Length: 40
Image (tube, rainbow, N blue to C red; front, side):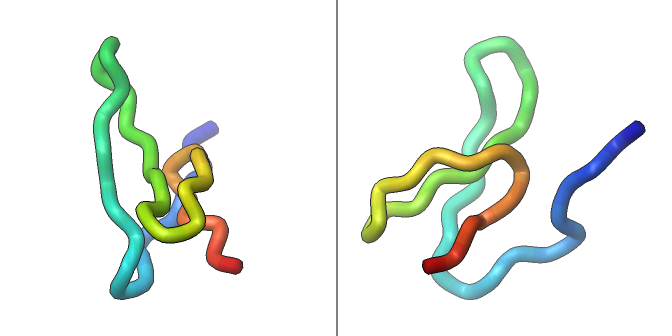
């Protein structure tokens, strides 16, 4: 089943995989995540 994050906090960026998928990545913490901005 589908599992992600409806909305994201003001600071995280939203990118797309080289295949079509969608993922997120932090610019400050520089941490890679999956459709979920793992704030820290």
